[PDB]
Length: 168
Length: 228
Image 1: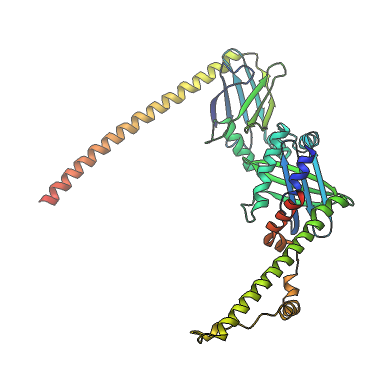
Image 2: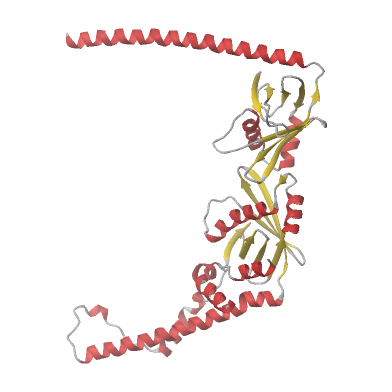
């Protein structure tokens, strides 16, 4: 069970950012669930193994390469030089992302999301997940810093004893 | 536009193409307005000229999901093809295949662009008698005549050198090294020896690789002179 939250700039209104959370069990190959939000209303959708396999077959692409490209585009895996452009038609509830390639654009994925009646629940769940992960990271950092300080003190003591021994 | 593409194709050198155990000789000229292609296999010559509308339609039909202006498509095709044609043994990224229709030829090219598939298809009809003649026969004719003139000039130079060697031998000292002696040159004897011995291998066309590898500069010069 893993989930990643990313920020995106929809071309329709490139002034206010949106947040997309994608969660998967083991890898994106089997499938995942995606949820787009902007702070007021949210949409949700799911992609299964059959859907991703069909999309890859339509692309005449290797499954591994397609999975890697999807991971790069959705999990904010921006490379040294690569731009991905996303857009979500609200009227048709159709969200699709393409790989802009310097005046030649290659559409990468497209799905139809359903407007969830309750956006408050999903926003609250996202906030709760963020708070949990930040607390866990803070605890891990504190523990690691304490361990590093203790190890540094021990190393200093051992170095001093070694200097004394070599002198004697 | 049309004349520009025709002239660009005419003033281009032949390149070697290897695809699925088959070999071809290809001339390509790309431009923002369209492209011209002339392929051959030493038995038949196919020519295809495509403008903006046709390239756009074919790209949309083949690449269902590649929206781009036709000029960008032409530029990408040029960037993909020209380096491969210019130099062989290039990093293998452009795969080619040829399907011989009863009348036409379908050349399918599949390549990678930033890790994404890129397909294109050349639908080449049989080259017109005038185009094939102007592109192969007359230029080859000029190269043959130019090489004959070169051989004649080299024979004259050999005659001068042989005369001067005779002058040295008539009044001169012995050779420091005797292994450097050379017999007098005879045009008839040399021609007969070459024809009898090395013509079978010298004239072996094979699949066309030696022609592109050896004397493309002479072909380009002859074609450029013919243009003027």
